[PDB]
Length: 279
Ligand SMILES: [Ca+2]
Ligand SMILES: [Ca+2]
Image (cartoon, rainbow, N blue to C red; front, side, top):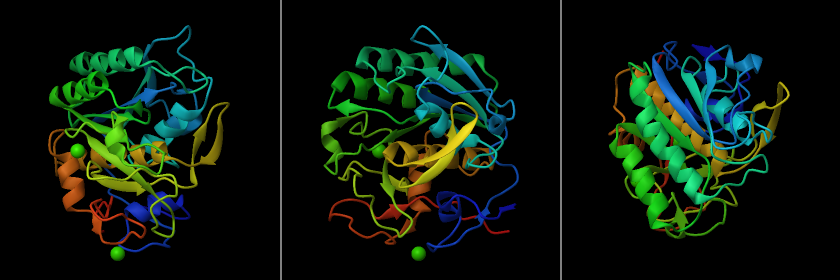
């Protein structure tokens, strides 16, 4: 398959070079995988989700995304026009409030929820969780992410937007999950992206167009936008049978574009997520 005039990040993950405009991908498109978007929720009625999204848990008064952020992230995972894995099933877990905030106790509960809830879903090609969230270092938050991974879920987490070492942020700093930095369309590390030895991979995160609440779309930026590129890419590769929940991060790293990025600090990986699709 080939989506012309795609969002630049979609084009970028299917090219060895920046500046292309077509997203080339296998038509299997993540069918048979499942991705949990642990965030502010998902506006599952958005036309772009085509009935493939649903809310499965909320920690607030409503299951509605009153923010947009979780809808955006879910769009980059799996919407028709904006998504990496355009036929995956999406599951919404609302652990963040409508201002985008949440307490670590809630975030932890949400992760343990996914670990159990996946055992009651039919996800024959495997299960991924996308966590575009975090704050300062917490060993309990890291332990929760490690448990989620251990349970058989491909966990992708944002590196954080502090232009600092991700060692001091959670769940970014949990070594066993996949920690995602952000890049821009000119293959620079994004100005706000965290860095550090704990990063596994970079994905597109500056000026990312996706779905928004009220059946709308917009462009926003952050390691939160990079993370769902990786999570959708994992689901895509798991449906193709190339990798498993346990091995996907390492697979993506090993098959990344290497050495493409600028302003990567020594000791941080120079690796950009890449689907290695050949028609
Ligand atoms: Ca290159
Ligand atoms: Ca890691």
